[PDB]
Image (tube, rainbow, N blue to C red):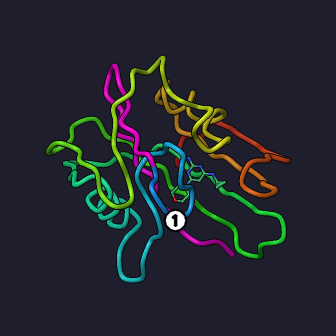
């Protein structure tokens, strides 16, 4: 059994947009925009809503780029994160009570201030390859196991 989450990376030819999470789960780390998928909305719908909520941005089209399953030791539910990509954004990103958005050059991505798994799968995101990932965490900092592969269908 797993719970659905979304994650949205606005990835342009020279830069990626990230947000500093100000409260809640993952506070103090840069990440893409996303969160819990709600009852009554598609996964992509949930992805658009969290992007609008956390950055004010809306998007013409979202593209499926990956799926990452997380297990946390001692927690019965798995985290199933659907990762989306997009180039063209509508609007200017602005701080919310969840996220302080900033653009990053692609050689200055702050992996040390991100979730530790991102160092593993973000490269596949940059090569525009679809991927499936699995990470077993102890706490929120320690990866104990992981698998990562390229897929033809996310
Ligand atoms: N890039 C990334 N790495 C994560 N690592 C797992 C917590 C250990 C979680 C996560 N998000 C989870 C919540 O919804 C947004 C995506 N995003």
**8 part of magenta stretch:** yes
The correct choice, above or below, for 116 with respect to 71 in the image is above
The correct choice, above or below, for 44 with respect to 104 in the image is below
**What's the residue at 33%, 31% (across, down)?**
103
| Mark 1 residue element | loop
Q: Is residue 106 left or right of residue 120?
A: left
Quadrant where the N terminus sits is bottom right
**What's the residue at 79%, 47% (across, down)?**
142
Give the number of callouts.
Answer: 1
Predominant secondary structure, magenta span: strand
Q: Quadrant of residue 38?
A: bottom left
Circle 1 crowding by C-alpha within 10 Å: few under 14, some 14–19, many from 20? few
Where on the image, by quarter, is ligand 1? bottom right
The residue furthest bottom is 39
**Circle 1 sits on which residue?**
24
**What's the residue at 46%, 63% (across, down)?**
35
Q: Is residue 48 left or right of residue 19?
A: left
Q: Position of residue 47 (x, y in %)?
A: 37, 60
**34 part of magenta stretch:** no
Q: Position of residue 88 (x, y in %)?
A: 21, 37
Residue 64 seen: no
Magenta segment range?
Answer: 1-20
Q: Is mark 1 within 8 Å of ligand 1?
A: no
The correct choice, above or below, for 116 with respect to 74 in the image is above
Q: Quadrant of residue 116?
A: top right
In-front residue for pair 90/86 = 90
**What's the residue at 53%, 29% (across, down)?**
110
Q: Position of residue 137 (x, y in %)?
A: 78, 54
Q: Position of residue 96 (x, y in %)?
A: 30, 57
Q: Is residue 125 left or right of residue 8?
A: right
In-front residue for pair 70/139 = 139
């Amino acid at each position: 059994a797993s719970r659905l989450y979304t994650l949205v990376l606005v990835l342009q030819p020279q830069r990626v947009l990230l947000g500093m999470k100000k409260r809640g789960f993952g506070a103090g780390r840069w990440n893409g925009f996303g969160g819990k998928v709600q009852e009554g909305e598609t996964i992509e719908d949930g992805a658009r809503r969290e992007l609008q909520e956390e950055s004010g941005l809306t998007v013409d089209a979202l593209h499926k780029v990956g799926q990452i399953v997380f297990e946390f030791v001692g927690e019965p539910e798995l985290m199933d994160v659907h990762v989306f990509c997009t180039d063209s954004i509508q609007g200017t990103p602005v701080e919310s009570d969840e996220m302080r958005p900033c653009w990053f050059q692609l050689d200055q991505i702050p992996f040390k201030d991100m979730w530790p798994d991102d160092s593993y799968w973000f490269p596949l995101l940059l090569q525009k390859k679809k991927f499936h990932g699995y990470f077993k965490f102890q706490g929120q900092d320690t990866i104990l196991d992981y698998t990562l592969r390229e897929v033809d269908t996310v």
